[PDB]
Image (cartoon, rainbow over all chains, first blue to last red; front, top):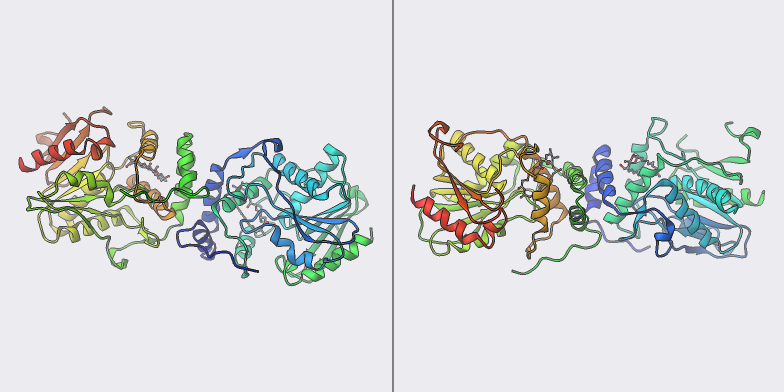
Length: 276
Length: 276
Ligand SMILES: C[C@H]1[C@@H]2C[C@@H](O)/C=C/C=C/C=C/C=C/C[C@@H](C)OC(=O)C[C@H](O)/C=C/C[C@H](O)C[C@](O)(C[C@@H]1O)O2
Ligand SMILES: C[C@H]1[C@@H]2C[C@@H](O)/C=C/C=C/C=C/C=C/C[C@@H](C)OC(=O)C[C@H](O)/C=C/C[C@H](O)C[C@](O)(C[C@@H]1O)O2
């Protein structure tokens, strides 16, 4: 609930936010990219001291447990799934995972497969040998889907399901299908109290993680998959997909679905989860 | 004498300095450029509240007074000419000028002519109607030379002289004549106590000011000009130049000439100044 410190005048955050405010998206992006390129990398998860650590956000008797993956945004983190987890308090366990590289002097993944890999392992630590559902908002969805598929292919472990909260793509290829530019504006122009500053490490991590979306290795997971679509933004999956993929609509936008319209989203997730 | 705070881990300074340490010059440069592009600009000196303000570094009876122009470096500023001015203490007045845009929420010049212009005006405030010599170390030299010429052409005011301390070029065109990359390393790897952090405003200002070197409008000044060359780095000007230009050698490198070998440099400046 407590606000992080406001951005200073000379801060990267402010310069960044001012650039978005004044519609200078490409320039802001190029700064991020140039900054992100200086960050040090890691190629294997063994080169990591410890794996990112999960935050428990709700506890409960059970069903499958919910493991949420943070969005690769500079203001992202475990706190992003707290309202959502509030609707599950006392019913089931809900964790969230930070992404590696957003905390100062964490190295970033060197490659998209390493990125998927670290999310997958850290998802496993969080499962603690239980049966789990991977959740991911927006592009965290893409990392959740693909981490499910990596778990299946290389460790023969299988989530009960994967939930995508308005995930718009996997690779997020910049190609006119969606205003990616306007979505970035809207995200960072959302008006709420964040518990984190957009540090230089978090902004450079965002660039690196977002930059890897375009080069992700696409891989199928057989486990069931729920896409909750947000109706305020506005028959592709059947028997021929090779696995069940359901699409539910929610009366919410992309942002409101994990915020004020979160309890709807949670309930659509509950309904679906037990109908499995 | 007191050290500025050390760079934090997440600071632009550290990431920047680490990039230079590990020989990743182009990448460091690209970050600087991308950052510098977000800074706001100004096209006229009238759009400025106040002009940069001079710091008096030595006082004295007189001769021509010495006005030093700071180097467009992130750790630059009036303090750069303090050792030099120490050798002139009690003999003549020595000021230094900050460059606009290095202090947080100063705007940068929009164009190289504005850059020259602001240096020229701020040089004038510092002259206080007296007779003066413009001094400039390295690339500050280029701005000093050209500001002399702007003073001459548009206000008919004429420095007594211009002194260039190992200035290597005017436009500093990246073109194999000199290791610009290795000179940037060496500058920032110099080991001394700075009284300033390389803030984000100072690093973005450096990019913008350095970036404008390549597009400067070259213009002659008629006033006499001394180039002190540094011998540890290792007949072009005569009657056909159209004005007197002298080249003296000093037993010093590019950095040592304003540091430990400063009193030599000062004395070469004294000798020359009175032989006019
Ligand atoms: C150099 C990289 C560059 C890195 C950097 O320049 C861009 C950073 C963009 C950050 C966008 C943040 C948006 C967050 C809002 C969130 C809802 O969208 C998202 O969660 C996903 C977001 O819309 C998609 C981002 C993909 C990047 O836009 C792809 C790319 O340009 C590919 C390029 O190869 O990233
Ligand atoms: C995008 C710009 C870029 C801006 C940014 O990418 C470069 C910053 C470079 C900073 C260098 C600092 C060196 C300081 C040492 C000092 C002794 O050298 C100097 O006082 C002068 C220094 O060697 C010359 C710098 C000229 C720039 O190197 C020219 C340029 O690449 C032209 C290009 O159009 O600057």
